[PDB]
Structures are given as C-alpha cells and as structure tokens.
Length: 219
Length: 231
Picture 1 (cartoon, rainbow over the protein chains, first blue to last red):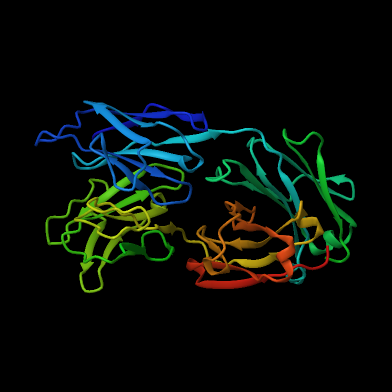
Picture 2 (cartoon, rainbow over the protein chains, first blue to last red; picture 1 turned 120 degrees about the horizontal axis):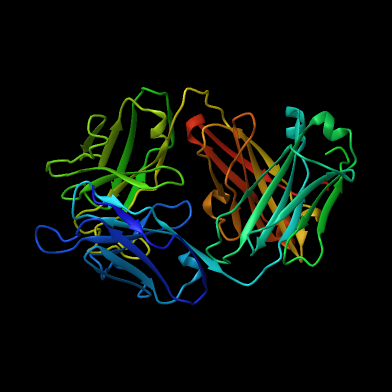
C-alpha cells in the first residue's frame, strides 16, 4: 500500500503567520494516465473531514485562497499564507491514484496566542443527584489561553486527592483558548458531613491562586 | 441542499455484525460514488472501500474484504455498509463520503463541481458490556457562576456507556459560548461529561435554557431545563 507520512509533527504558530505541512509518499503519486491525484483535508475537532485541495494545486470550491498546495513526485506541501483561529485542527493528506487509498498520520496545527487568565465557576450538587445517593461538585475554568492549568479541590480547608476527574477542551476555533472542567464526586453522606466546598485554581494568567467556594446549605 | 446523514451510534457484541446507513439529500445516489472510511478515535483514517452507484465494481480494502458488504437503496437514496465478525479492534467512528458527480447545492461553502461531501459519522463500539443510559443533572447558575456580569450554566451527563453522547442547547438554537467537554472515565468503567454555556446574567430571568442530551446506544433523549437557584 502506498505510504503517506506528514513531515511536521506538531506546529505552534502565531496568528496571521504562515504555516506549511509536508506529506511524503513512498511511491510516485503519478497515475497510469499521467496526472497526480493528491488530496488535502482539514478536520476540525470532533468534525468530519472536509476536503480542501485536490491534485496538488487544485483548490476545492469555497476553500479559502489562503490555502495553497504544491507537490512534486513523492513530496507535497500544503501552505496557509496567514493563519486564523478557525484553522486550528488536524490536516491529513489522501491519495486517490492507487487502491487502496492512503492517508497520512495527520498533523495537528495549534495556535500561539497571548496569555489569558481563566474565569472560575463553582457549581454545587443538585438535589436530584443527592436523591440518587451521590453528590458531584463542578469547578469550571473558562477561556484560558496557556493550556497548562492547576485545580485543587478542598473540603473544609482539607485538600482532597482522588474522587476528582477533569477534562480539557480542544482549542477554541474562535478564541484559540482552552477550557477546563473538574468534578469532585462524593457520596451523599460524605457531602453532608462537611460545610465548605471550594476549588482553588492556579494559572499563569492569574497573579495569585483564585479560589471559588460555597457552603453546603444542604445542596 | 446536499445533505449526508448517517445512522445513530451503535454498540455491538464481539463476533456480531454492524450496519450503518448513509442517506443522501438534494441529489440522487446515481453516478455518485460512495466511500467508507474508518477513523479510530484519536488515530488515523482507514479507507474501507468504495461502492459505485451505477453498478460499477466496488473495491474493498484487503483488510476488510471478507467482512464488508456494501449495498444501495436508490429509492431511499441510502447506501449501506455492513461489517461482520466484529472484533474489539473495530470500535471506531465510521464515515461515508459522497465523492461523485456534482453536488450542485452550496451547503454553506458551495461544493459545486467538486465531489466530496462527508457524513457526520457513526460511532460503533464492540463490547460485551451492558449499555447504560446517562443521568442528566443541572449545573444551575448562581452568584458562584457569575463573573463580570456573565453567568455560567450547564448540564452534567453522568455514568453512561458506550462513549457517544450528543448535547445541544435550546434545540440547537444556542451555540455561541457553548463548551461540551470530552468525557471522563469513572473507575466504574462508565463515562461522564459536562456541557456548559456562558450567557448574560441579566437575561437569567427572561431566557429559557434547555440542554438536549441524546445517547443513541441507550435509546435516551432527555431535555433538562437549567434554572438558577440557591448558592
């Protein structure tokens, strides 16, 4: 099977700055007719892939002029003259010249942006969940740029370890920022045995660790 | 309008078969080539095979030759992919790509003479485990949810299996400022997830926020209205 490997591993690029991904094929992409059929597709996070280029220079309709493609033999390169927040994603290279069609491993295009402190929100557990027997507390870190972020669950000044799970969003296609969500789950009994539930967030954009807290109040 | 729609997410037992549908809207499934591409989550794209609508020969990848069958219902405009003797290595998102003729319709950026349009995807999980519906609780806005005049609300989709759960807001009318987080795996082996949205706190009294959660494997559709209360 024709092999497709994308030279750039990962790419942190400044906004409005150019970018270029390389694709390498083990065998010639020229077909038995005399053409070369190479496609470039962009997949935004959690989306189906959208075809941007065909052949090497042929740009699909509705595809921005910022995208351009140029290849020779076994090497091919996709270039974005200027990079916008909407370009974040994974770029793949497909070949339709020979069966079975091949895809590159893909290449993630990230975005370098100025630091942004997160906004912290704390959510207490709902009564319905307490009826089910459990209690989940959620700490939300919204629109922070540096991906690295620290979250700490404290119950009545007592630091916790375990019983917490968190997820980070894929880079925003508008802000180019990130969002974090951390849930601390306890039993109803454990939850009632305490008074103050707080989460202390530390991030680069934060001059000093911000803590969002609340008093059970039976909920 | 050229619209490609696919079956809902499915969960199948090892050694069983899986069937997914690709329905084409706005253009007859004639002289329009259909392709099936598999994507392992957080992995590469694998081209399963192509099916020619006007009875041309249909080529299957050497990998899936014995296990994949492709068929077309021209009347309903739906192509079908069927993969049998499923193995755990088969758990992935399945796509059908309409790569043929001229789409004709814009579909936001106009596809026009171009051929490719892609399906939304069908998540297929191969596992003997029991399917479990998600539990949806509200993440009510409060003084603890407000910053600089903006309030944050959401929905907690807890303890579901398998993985695919879709969350929408106000039946899809609300998408600005929405964050649906990737799911986490509890020690229990069940997934949990959260979806939040930032809205003007002044509006909290006048607007209605409802989160729409669909867990097709479980066959569950829940609409939970998130309203501000307490602390």
